[PDB]
Image (cartoon, rainbow, N blue to C red; front, side):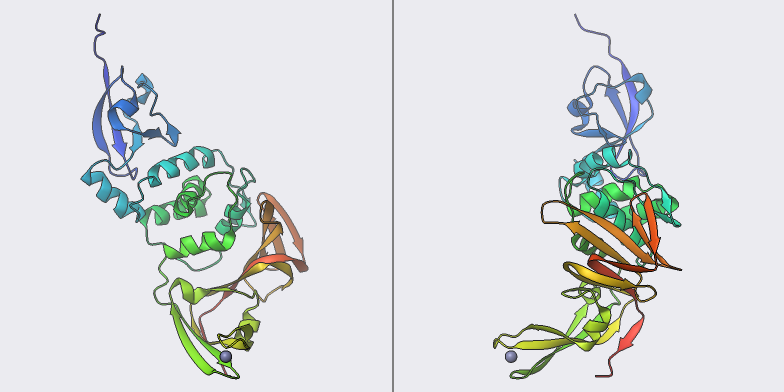
Length: 317
Ligand SMILES: [Zn+2]
């Protein structure tokens, strides 16, 4: 009747660093013993242990106080589905290719990941330190060329699944949310001919992102925005303290000039499907399109996001 019990030792984890010794019954599934369980991204919840599994590390969900703390300390989230979504993505991104293109880690196109490739390429050209150890650790590996965990983390943090259409501005917003931008400061002035002037200070992520124009110069000169009185008012940059700025707008034909920006994202398509490309300004203009690379002296296209170097700026207005 009853089969002789066989067991193996395995380790469970939520961060792949702190291991937790377990003894599993090879006649029960992982799911029956751990809840949802993953082996390097693969869902083994419904798998019964193999001898080859002995000594291997499995991710589980934070189901006790020790794992909850380890997971928060490593990822800076308490979203219950986070680890599941991170493993589900990782099962895909570990099969993506990450070619070095013009010295930067890119991503060969798959699974609508073009927005991720230009986000990744952008990160490697701006000064940014992540706060979660998971992002620090994974970004370091991504810079070295092994970007699978980093890309799966971006998907998890953004609540995007592999293959879902993503927006670069929104993705960067999530990444900046988890970065140290505390010393970034922006002072704006808005001037209405009827209502007068109103100055506003922004900090952190809101200090480095602007939605409305791609041109940093235009933002220094002034952009027209609605005023509550019904007139159009003029908003201009008074003071900026940050290592970069990101200027974003709905996709519009726009000319990129060598040496006047750091990098940019281009979006061809519509609200339901499209394709992002990346433009970086080095010795010439390089267009990185996943694994593909072209160059040109001028660039014009439907640009959505442009990144600029900064340190300290003060208006003369
Ligand atoms: Zn007004």
